[PDB]
Amino acid sequence: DAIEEKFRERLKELVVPKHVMDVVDEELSKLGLLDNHSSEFNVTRNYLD
Amino acid sequence: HRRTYVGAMPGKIIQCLKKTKTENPLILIDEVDKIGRGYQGDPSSALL
Image (tube, rainbow over the protein chains, first blue to last red):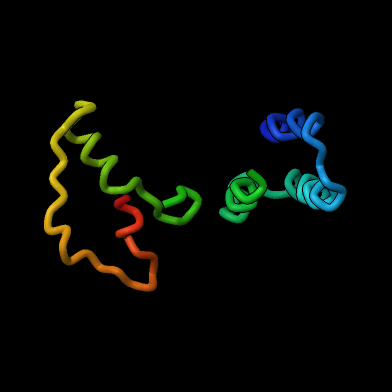
């Protein structure tokens, strides 16, 4: 979440469309659950980036 | 490769830069004429 801060803080200014905001919301919920070493975790991290 | 793929290693260029250890070597692309222009991702766009 610290790494995503660099995204969030930007989002405070440039409005996030309610669609996009909900999508990043569920991805933000999923992202913490994910194991640190699964290749899917690095993939979803790069995707969320 | 992306480094998230299994087995990813840096592209050819980085290896030459690693090898010559200077910032300004004399790269020599060889035999440009017959580069493979296929459906699997055309390098010729990558050269630009």
